[PDB]
Image (cartoon, rainbow, N blue to C red):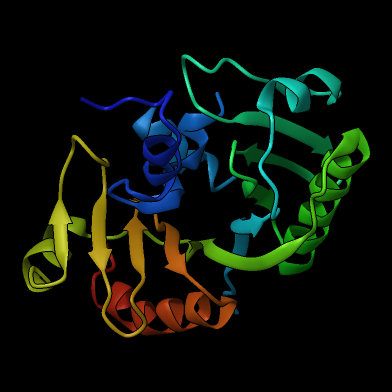
Length: 219
């Protein structure tokens, strides 16, 4: 009963995954591939930022798709226009309602700036679009503690906060409480941090987890 040519169902899909908008690449094109792409004196690094913009006016996606340069619109597959720009290299999903979702940036400034570009593009085509309600919805961070994790022991010891689920992910899924951050922990020591609303939460989730990962070093 999942229809992605529906608008209410296609927007809700981007944020309703197991990992919410971490999975946003599957709607602009594997489960394991989506995570591992987000890797490529230890300090985390921002790998993606998902933002939402309300453009304000009803949009005719056939028109938008026609006049946009690098753009794709198959309304049977997914119910939005897929537009891309080259700097900040990003991707936007533009709905019939003027809602817009903007992914690909790696700074909070690139996210807001890219979003302003997509909005201006849509105006220039000929719409009463105004850039409003810019919110950052998710920030994905990555980390590499550069030493291997005894995941099988961390899964037992922190079973309250952990799962091993090969179907979803080949490593450990750490659901941290404060801050509410899911850490995807690889056996090699690389980590993918998601859920964050501000970058502070990425560093906090990392500072919290580094002493835990140390206790579980494989030697």
